[PDB]
Image 1 (cartoon, rainbow, N blue to C red):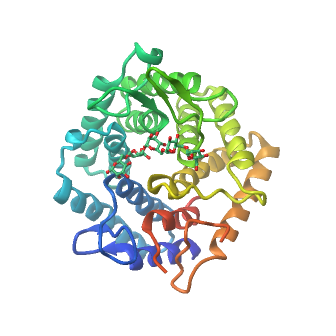
Image 2 (image 1 turned 90 degrees about the vertical axis):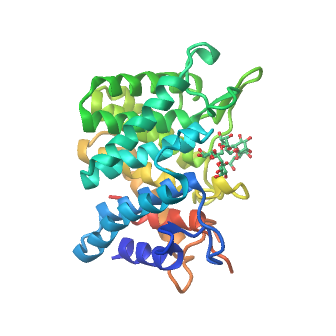
Length: 333
Ligand SMILES: *[C@]1(OC[C@H]2O[C@@H](O)[C@@H](O)[C@@H](O)[C@@H]2O)O[C@H](CO[C@H]2O[C@H](CO[C@H]3O[C@H](CO[C@H]4O[C@H](CO)[C@@H](O)[C@H](O)[C@@H]4O)[C@@H](O)[C@H](O)[C@@H]3O)[C@@H](O)[C@H](O)[C@@H]2O)[C@@H](O)[C@H](O)[C@@H]1O
């Protein structure tokens, strides 16, 4: 019941049923940012997939549609006017998942049209020998936060359509990103800036989307190297993006990063499921499971009386992005 309790509390605190959007914080003065709203959309989907309560499941399934509808009312159906390719791709990825859950073809169309806009027009072979640009306005940097989500979105589209076009895209994007945006041992770099080079700053959400795309490529291709890729990035996270007690770091004050544990936990759950199914990396699997469970318990021990957990997991206004990670964590496998 913990996942159910956490999701219900999150909705009670942050869901606006009038605007069909999440509030940015408990003051209820501003709705959540566009890109983060896609991530909260995926949280609703994860809760939907996790719960065993048929009543809550039906409510969450409806909410999947309402989140899309509330966003389209404010931002339109065509997001290609947004200069941030990642903003577009986070929504394309969400849309692909919403299709999988609802079977509603509008989500497949949203996913495919937006993925195609970004991949077909924003991939470049010249700078850095490959990669998708962060922006469709100015072309100055190629970033983990667009490239690995794009590989994930391609993998969802492959699974849905069976069109090898999308597997080929995922393979190509990931190969480039592994080569140019990692150290080869699981540290994912933030971006490569033209006239500068790589910026080797690691963050939770970029570890996460790298891990998720690697797991998805493992499953689609049968090539064990991808599982090894995922494990190295999980190990790096567990050892190097934690405090002295092994609790995942707080990445504030940056507003985009503060909630990044949400994306990380979503993707660590994918790795956990694949390790459990396959029996591969059994020693690491045991250590990883124990460490995940520890993080989750520590986070939830800081819940307030309304069952909301601030995103500083080691320690009056609660924010929906920062608070989402603890909810995500209870709505995994
Ligand atoms: C996309 O959203 C764009 C914009 O949309 C607006 O509507 C609104 O929602 C805004 O809030 C959105 O920004 O772009 C997001 C931002 O991407 C850029 O910025 C992030 C964060 O950059 C910072 O952090 C990195 C990483 O390292 C730093 O933090 C770590 C961890 O704490 C430290 O260890 C390290 O020392 C360092 O301090 C850093 O490299 C940057 O210089 C900067 O300090 C980057 O991660 C991106 O690559 C972009 O530069 C993005 O988060 C989303 O994808 C969103 O869709």
